[PDB]
Image: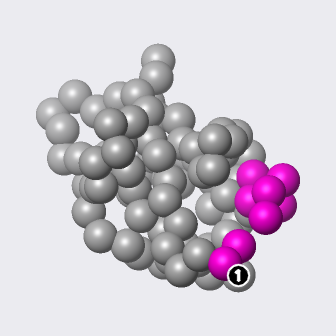
Amino acid sequence: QRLLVQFQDEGGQLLGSPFDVPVDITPDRLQLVCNALLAQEDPLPLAFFVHDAEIVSSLGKTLESQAETEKVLDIIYQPQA
């Protein structure tokens, strides 16, 4: 239902600290949180990935297609247009 997640850039660097999200969270809602953390003057659209699968609909949909023994789930973010 709720999962502890952690943002991570394409270079493997961690962004912020782990936080709880509902499993049904969408990429649009993840973009809002991530750009809040990045605090840029010109933020960019973001794509998100968990275990080498893109979150295109919701975190839960992508996780179902895989699978979870882990305690913190790394969500990789990547700028897109």
Which quarter of the figure has residue 53? Answer: top right
User: Which of the two residues, 20 or 26, is positioned nearer the viewer here?
Assistant: 20
- Whether residue 61 is visible to the viewer of this picture, yes or no, is no
User: Relative to 76, does residue 7 appear above or below in the rendering?
Assistant: below
Q: Is residue 67 magenta?
A: yes
Magenta portion: prevailing SS class: loop
Residue at 70% x, 81% y: name it: 1
Residue at 30% x, 55% y: name it: 14
- Where residue 72 appears, as percent x and y from the top left, is 49, 74
Side of 30 relative to 53 (left or right): left
Q: Which residue is the site of mark 1? A: 1
Secondary structure under the numbered disc 1 in the rendered image: loop
Which stretch did the figure color magenta?
Answer: 62-69
User: Relative to 79, does residue 40 appear above or below in the rendering?
Assistant: below
Residue at 39% x, 36% y: name it: 10
Residue at 70% x, 65% y: name it: 24
Query: Please, what is the three-letter code of the amino acid marked with disc 1?
Result: Gln
Q: Is residue 37 magenta?
A: no
- Where residue 32 appears, as percent x and y from the top left, is 42, 50
